[PDB]
Image (cartoon, rainbow, N blue to C red):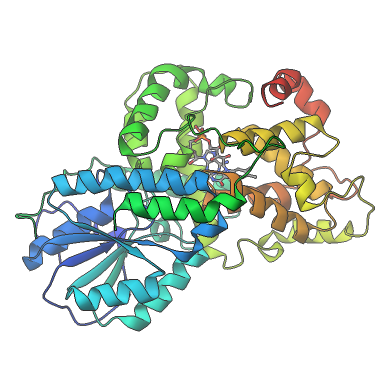
Length: 458
Ligand SMILES: Cc1cc2nc3c(=O)[nH]c(=O)nc-3n(C[C@H](O)[C@H](O)[C@H](O)COP(=O)(O)OP(=O)(O)OC[C@H]3O[C@@H](n4cnc5c(N)ncnc54)[C@H](O)[C@@H]3O)c2cc1C
């Protein structure tokens, strides 16, 4: 229960576990949505706390899986959290950063701090569901989750997997009047109930031996492309609206032009709300066509990616591809591939295709491949791999290791679109790739200045 007139739509919250309410603080286990503003999970947690006459507290688990990615993501995330600590303290909301995996750490925190209720935010990824299961086994209090990431709650937008954007889109657009709304201000707590610097230090030390390097031993990653944190995210949204949105409709498929929003690292870590971004873009007057194109990406393609992972347990595997695509890829499984590259050759940009290699260099060096070349890139991994299953493994591996926005439903769904035709149609049949949409080198040369892209990332 929340207080009357809390302005919380109950369809954004789902019970994970019934239990017996304790009498201590409401705990928001923050995971996907690392921000203090425009955060329905935090707002709901604050409202339940108010109704129960207790403070709200935030807990965040620094998990054992950080060593599966790189310094690039750890630093981006932790520097954000350092800023988040301050923002929350200004609301008199304490934040606790627990070192370990959530099953053990959240269970013990709930016991030690006498939590009344546990709330988390929503992710459809397997790792979050693994963590939920272990937490559920270790707690006796009620446990809710709130969809703070999507404008329309994932379980409301559709009751099933949607095979196409054109079947998801009408369902989603029909629910915006309900769910696309301004956010209330977060009410501070009535009174105030190892540093992150130390953690960051220790973690970087553990990641240093796996850092991506040039043959010169100097690191590949350039950390000045995306300043982390909630405040920077807002400035990137504002600069997009002011300077790039007008040209987005025309230039979003031109990787030589910096005309995308550059919001994905912030959106992935939840340092900015996609609902906020949509409210601000909807209010803007910009060139015809651009707003439509952008909203189709951040509403339909982003939220269909959560739809994909939520309703397909096997979202990272061949089995989740549509039937037409499985049958087509199977029919061509024994076709001789034109090339076969090792994961190390792909990783180092050592194929015979200079556009592919430049796309990989953009990823290595900036942590954000242009969205047009991500499609080209993944499709060539299919073409130059022993099987579609190996192609998925390679693409996921590289995406998750080197993208700042990786380890994300958008990535699994984008790789499945690219390799498996998920949310696509069948195209003309070719050897190796069957009826999966093909993106040729020469087609790219007709579309944009390939030589300039290669020079930029060489
Ligand atoms: C093989 C492949 C891998 C991808 N990997 C990721 C990934 O790891 N993480 C990730 O967040 N996105 C991924 N994408 C989707 C897309 O490429 C990026 O979201 C986009 O490039 C992000 O840059 P931006 O924020 O400047 O994009 P913008 O074009 O300005 O769009 C803004 C937001 O809309 C969303 N969006 C845009 N395009 C897509 C899309 N095709 N699918 C889903 N959402 C979209 C994103 O949240 C994006 O940040 C991938 C796509 C493909 C084909």
